Amino acid sequence: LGQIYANNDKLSKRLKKVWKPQLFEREFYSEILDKKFTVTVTMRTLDLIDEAYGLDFYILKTPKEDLCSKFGMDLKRGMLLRLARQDPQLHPEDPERRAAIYDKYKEFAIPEEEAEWVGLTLEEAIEKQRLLEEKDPVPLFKIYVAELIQQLQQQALSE
Amino acid sequence: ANFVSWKSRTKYTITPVKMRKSGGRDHTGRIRVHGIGGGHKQRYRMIDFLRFRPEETKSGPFEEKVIQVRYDPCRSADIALVAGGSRKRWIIATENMQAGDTILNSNHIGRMAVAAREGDAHPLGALPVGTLINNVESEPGRGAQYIRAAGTCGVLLRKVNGTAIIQLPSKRQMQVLETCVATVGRVSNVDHNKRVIGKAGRNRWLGKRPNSGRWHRKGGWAGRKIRPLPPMKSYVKL
RNA sequence: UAGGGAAUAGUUUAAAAAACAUCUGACUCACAUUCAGAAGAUGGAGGUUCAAUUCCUCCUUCCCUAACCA
RNA sequence: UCCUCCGCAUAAGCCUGCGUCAGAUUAAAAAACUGACAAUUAACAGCCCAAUAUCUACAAUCAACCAACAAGUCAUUAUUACCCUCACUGUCAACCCAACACAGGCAUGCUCAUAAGGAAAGGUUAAAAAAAGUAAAAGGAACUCGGCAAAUCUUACCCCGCCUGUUUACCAAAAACAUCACCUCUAGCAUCACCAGUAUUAGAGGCACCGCCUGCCCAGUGACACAUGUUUAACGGCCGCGGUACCCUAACCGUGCAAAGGUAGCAUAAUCACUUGUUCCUUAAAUAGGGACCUGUAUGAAUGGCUCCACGAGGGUUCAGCUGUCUCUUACUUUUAACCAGUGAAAUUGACCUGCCCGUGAAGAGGCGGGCAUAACACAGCAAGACGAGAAGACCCUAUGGAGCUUUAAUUUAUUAAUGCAAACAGUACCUAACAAACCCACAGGUCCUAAACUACCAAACCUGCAUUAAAAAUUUCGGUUGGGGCGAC
RNA sequence: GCUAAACCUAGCCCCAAACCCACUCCACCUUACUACCAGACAACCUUAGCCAAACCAUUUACCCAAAUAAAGUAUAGGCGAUAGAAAUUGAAACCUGGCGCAAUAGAUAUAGUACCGCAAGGGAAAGAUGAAAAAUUUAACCAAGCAUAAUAUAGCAAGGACUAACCCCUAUACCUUCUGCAUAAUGAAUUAACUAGAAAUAACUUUGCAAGGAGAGCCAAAGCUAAGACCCCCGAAACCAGACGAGCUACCUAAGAACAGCUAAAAGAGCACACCCGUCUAUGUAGCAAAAUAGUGGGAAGAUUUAUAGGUAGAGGCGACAAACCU
Ligand SMILES: C[NH+](C)c1cc(NC(=O)CNC(C)(C)C)c(O)c2c1C[C@H]1C[C@H]3[C@H]([NH+](C)C)C(O)=C(C(N)=O)C(=O)[C@@]3(O)C(O)=C1C2=O
Ligand SMILES: [K+]
Ligand SMILES: [K+]
Ligand SMILES: [K+]
Ligand SMILES: [K+]
Ligand SMILES: [K+]
Ligand SMILES: [K+]
Ligand SMILES: [K+]
Ligand SMILES: [K+]
Ligand SMILES: [K+]
Ligand SMILES: [K+]
Ligand SMILES: [Mg+2]
Ligand SMILES: [Mg+2]
Ligand SMILES: [Mg+2]
Ligand SMILES: [Mg+2]
Ligand SMILES: [Mg+2]
Ligand SMILES: [Mg+2]
Ligand SMILES: [Mg+2]
Ligand SMILES: [Mg+2]
Ligand SMILES: [Mg+2]
Ligand SMILES: [Mg+2]
Ligand SMILES: [Mg+2]
Ligand SMILES: [Mg+2]
Ligand SMILES: [Mg+2]
Ligand SMILES: [Mg+2]
Ligand SMILES: [Mg+2]
Ligand SMILES: [Mg+2]
Ligand SMILES: [Mg+2]
Ligand SMILES: [Mg+2]
Ligand SMILES: [Mg+2]
Ligand SMILES: [Mg+2]
Ligand SMILES: [Mg+2]
Ligand SMILES: [Mg+2]
Ligand SMILES: [Mg+2]
Ligand SMILES: [Mg+2]
Ligand SMILES: [Mg+2]
Ligand SMILES: [Mg+2]
Ligand SMILES: [Mg+2]
Ligand SMILES: [Mg+2]
Ligand SMILES: [Mg+2]
Ligand SMILES: [Mg+2]
Ligand SMILES: [Mg+2]
Ligand SMILES: [Mg+2]
Ligand SMILES: [Mg+2]
Ligand SMILES: [Mg+2]
Ligand SMILES: [Mg+2]
Ligand SMILES: [Mg+2]
Ligand SMILES: [Mg+2]
Ligand SMILES: [Mg+2]
Ligand SMILES: [Mg+2]
Ligand SMILES: [Mg+2]
Ligand SMILES: [Mg+2]
């Protein structure tokens, strides 16, 4: 979203101008996820995926601010979780092939704890955090029956 | 704002359905077409424009009896209630269609053309060249969109290469596949264009609002323009 | 009242020609047409310019437009 | 005694807003004021339905007979599911929208005439002027811009518009707009307008029923075709200069110019140089009106021309009558008025102890000069002055002040459409010079001054980026001088 | 002597410091504040313009993360108006204070209430004894306006006077605006309160230090540091952005309602009520009324009139074009 001077002359009228990218619908296969995706892309994305030697490399290498898509960051979290877990759901019947994929991408492996939070928006993260912390309250009946026993137990040992 | 099209019913009936006026507004509530508004209330009678529509468990040519020919507020032509088997439907009446007639709905094309009786529906390939036809479709099974107004007809001009050339009421030629169905004869109410509105108020009865009083100076578009007939429109794919 | 334009053979148009009118002849019984000859004007006055049909300035003359707001 | 619009209900609105008691004191004068306490009770009304499929051509009008078009408000069945029974809310009033206890606005039913609902006069006097009425001698439009208003209850016509209709709420109702009719333009088609339509259609416009017509012009400008072009019921336009029958005029003559040279009609007026033309009607008298003629600075054909029925709160002319319009006013009634009592506004106002005449003066003095007049103060009238009041003149000019509108004003194409190109993506390629010199098989046949290189449309109606042309718009300005400005001139 | 007058609190202002705010039982996104049914609707997207440039058309400062300094320098710009860095440099922690207001001030605030507006929105006014009111009996005197107490030839209202108020003589209000105003040019009933000159450059004056000055930076060929001293108020028609508006009115949608009698009978026919409209006259003109009343009118089965709910929204709508109507 910008402006332009008509006929590239500052003394002419200043006009609003929007340059939009040329978008193509193409399909892409993920080795780690063993899935085909129909993604809207630019010609640039296709040039970047080539320079990365594939979609898995492109998603795994490119950082958040250069992917510029929540979908790319979900693909990353997805790929990263299979690598962190060595997930056997990838080609369940081909352990040899499955290990060739995971070795190919061994550079990007991170702990599963960290991979779960990769790409989450702040609002997603809080919901993830709120759900992890969602626990039913403990009835005070159980809490006091523990204090009583421990209170009776300590009294017995002393004498 | 909250405009909802009346054309919401999904099953064919012959019961006249209530329709809602638009006033020439679109769904935004804004005037889209000027000069529409008011008029007598009307009910819509669903016209079946697919003449060769065999019943659910039936197939092939079939006949129908004309039960009634009556007035239609929603179009300039007349409509005929026909009954065949266990089904009734509204169709466009032809010039001389009357109660008690029997009409033929056929999809058969033979080496020899049939004798074209008014009110019968045949594929274009089955008709003699020069027959007067109405209620034409552009693709086989699409349903009649052409030659539907009162007193109208087209002419079968040629039958070449499994296609039929016809002349539209506007005199422009139109090419379709020979399996397209048409009805023989002219649409009913042949004297419809001789009607005299008579007084301004009768145009209000028909749902027309008066023209703007604003004066417009005529521009280059005005004045007689003698241009050739457009080239034949083809709906055939090679 | 105030601005603009225009005055070319008798006529009407050109840029000093043309068609008429006129004059002379031929053709005709005669006339007309036609044919062949001939003459015929740059509004007047005032300039300049190497040279004034496009240029003056004025007069004389005819036209055109404008003459509005309270 | 008088009035009667009314009134009573429902709806909507409003929300305790003339019940009681106790207070104060009741109201544009003398409780609807304050505080307490009461109060409208459901049958009327509101608040409603288990599912899925399926059904539903035949108006209404006393619905019969007839006759219509603008073609219409009222309907199920099948099979499952289904024991449970009167909750909740409105219910008052002298009421609401109009700043008000406002002559306004306000839907339906019923009565209207009333069974219901109300009081025009605070008391007096009975001047002007003013308002609203009634009556009026003789005359009867002499009034006046006009018969406005009144009275009476008429005739004939002219213009314009055909007609009913529509409009500037709050200065214009009209001749303006629409309109039946006629014609021009665009469009071959569906699932949100047009339209559940389909060229006898549907959109954009002109003009204005009907009758008689609607002439000529495509050069220019626009549209369309963009191959010579087509198109006026598109924008528009539709000739001169000389001469010839006494004059007038020119059937006629000469020459020139244009795309065509204004045709048919019509013309002393919604139209008007002279002009109040001229003539015939009309009056005693006509710058009026009618009929004609003259003929058009600048009449004229769907920017419609010319007639004509009917119609009009349109503009104009008129017979008869009618009358206070007038000659020429008068009389009476009510209102207002004036006086008494109650209540009690507004604009306005430098201060005022606020005369006249002449003169003067920022050019029209109560106020200055010179004269003249002159105890003081209420009330009623009047409208000559106070350049009276009201609204920082709507005229006119000025302001490098606005704004609306229109364009061939300048700037621009963001947007929109079309087009090209590039991007994306089909998806496969050998297709235009034979000429027999003793050498040539009984045939599908060798050579000489000719036996060659040899991508097809870039690969769709999309989307992006670039240009290009349009349409629609947007932003901004509209110099000065000037014996006011404009115009002219500078 | 009335009406009045007077008051000192309520609170408020600017800083500092410190990082605030929940259910309170029941109700509340449907017509909010409404115990209790089959759904799926979902957020993001450059401000513009006034104004300055004495028009206007490119352009015209707007905290963006340390005071100072570099520097109004580099640079940008119808190279105009104006705009304008960076490198580099690197001062300071002690909340409870005030040469702030004191009822027309200070918050709009006693309250976002009353009141006004359909809505968005706009938006007030005011109190005052005393230790005790379970002491109601103790003070003056003060604006305009009045009252006590109208008035006596003559004149900007006074002045000079005078024994004497007046009589005599002299004397053309004021402000603004103008060549020039008693002007019959502007404004002003009057009282009270409120209500309008803000700062650089250079210079000057008065100190300090002085070839130096200055508490880094900046100036210096008597400079340099410091100080003093200086440039108003109210007013358009507009322009743009985002909201709110169709309970009026224009047009439309859904579904209603009304239209007596008489004539004629095909009905946008006639007469004529209810009803709708508004031709003409008079009245009224701060009205009864921010468009009415009386009479007279036009239409009144229709392109009629009208109740209800809904729709279209300002670069817009709507329009039988009147540039109509859109509270
Ligand atoms: C002053 N002249 C130019 C003139 C003026 C007017 N009218 C006006 O100027 C009106 N002006 C207003 C609009 C009122 C401001 C005019 O109205 C006229 C005329 C011209 C005459 C010429 C007449 C002439 N004859 C008959 C004396 C004549 O020969 C012709 C002719 N065409 O050749 C006429 O038509 C003539 O009769 C005529 O009509 C004239 C005007 O109408
Ligand atoms: K009228
Ligand atoms: K006349
Ligand atoms: K005459
Ligand atoms: K009329
Ligand atoms: K007077
Ligand atoms: K003068
Ligand atoms: K300006
Ligand atoms: K004066
Ligand atoms: K003056
Ligand atoms: K004045
Ligand atoms: Mg039309
Ligand atoms: Mg029109
Ligand atoms: Mg007279
Ligand atoms: Mg007279
Ligand atoms: Mg009258
Ligand atoms: Mg006309
Ligand atoms: Mg009006
Ligand atoms: Mg009206
Ligand atoms: Mg007005
Ligand atoms: Mg009127
Ligand atoms: Mg008209
Ligand atoms: Mg006609
Ligand atoms: Mg014509
Ligand atoms: Mg003629
Ligand atoms: Mg006449
Ligand atoms: Mg004239
Ligand atoms: Mg004339
Ligand atoms: Mg003309
Ligand atoms: Mg025309
Ligand atoms: Mg008629
Ligand atoms: Mg009428
Ligand atoms: Mg008349
Ligand atoms: Mg008479
Ligand atoms: Mg006067
Ligand atoms: Mg005055
Ligand atoms: Mg003024
Ligand atoms: Mg300006
Ligand atoms: Mg401006
Ligand atoms: Mg200029
Ligand atoms: Mg000037
Ligand atoms: Mg002048
Ligand atoms: Mg000029
Ligand atoms: Mg002056
Ligand atoms: Mg004065
Ligand atoms: Mg003045
Ligand atoms: Mg005054
Ligand atoms: Mg601007
Ligand atoms: Mg009538
Ligand atoms: Mg209307
Ligand atoms: Mg108009
Ligand atoms: Mg106008």
Image (tube, coloured by chain):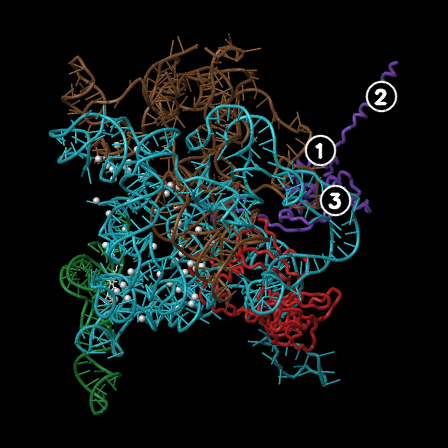
Chain colours: A purple, B red, C green, D cyan, E brown
Q: CA distance from mark 1 to mark 3?
A: 30 Å
The mark nearer the N terminus, 2 or 3, is: 3
Count neighbours of disc 3 (C-alpha within 10 A) and say few if under 14, some if 14 to 19, many if 20 or more: many
- Classify residue E103 as left or right of residue D481: right
Asked whether the beta carbons under mark 2 and mark 1 sit within 8 Å of each other, the answer is no
Q: Amino acid at mark 2?
A: Ile
Q: CA distance from mark 2 to mark 1?
A: 34 Å
Q: CA distance from mark 2 to mark 3?
A: 54 Å
Asked whether the beta carbons under mark 1 and mark 3 sit within 8 Å of each other, the answer is no
Q: Measured along the vertical axis of the image, is residue E315 above or below residue D122? A: below
Dot 3: element: loop
Say which quarter of the image contains residue D424. bottom right
Q: Are the numbered discs 2 and 1 placed on the same chain, yes or no?
A: yes
Using the image, name the chain to which the residue with label 2 belongs.
A
- Classify residue B182 as left or right of residue E237: right
Dot 2: element: helix
Total marks in image = 3
Q: Amino acid at mark 1?
A: Arg
Comparing B28 with C31, the one in front is B28
Q: Amino acid at mark 3?
A: Ile
Residue at position x 75%, y 65% in the image? B57
Q: Position of residue D7 (x, y in %)?
A: 51, 44
The mark nearer the N terminus, 2 or 1, is: 1
The mark nearer the N terminus, 1 or 3, is: 3
- Numbered badge on residue A149: 2
Using the image, name the chain to which the residue with label 1 belongs.
A
Count neighbours of disc 2 (C-alpha within 10 A) and say few if under 14, some if 14 to 19, many if 20 or more: few
Comparing D418 with B81, the one in front is B81
Comparing B66 with A103, the one in front is B66
Which of the two discs, 2 and 3, sits closer to the camera? 2
The residue tagged 3 is: A32
The residue tagged 1 is: A130
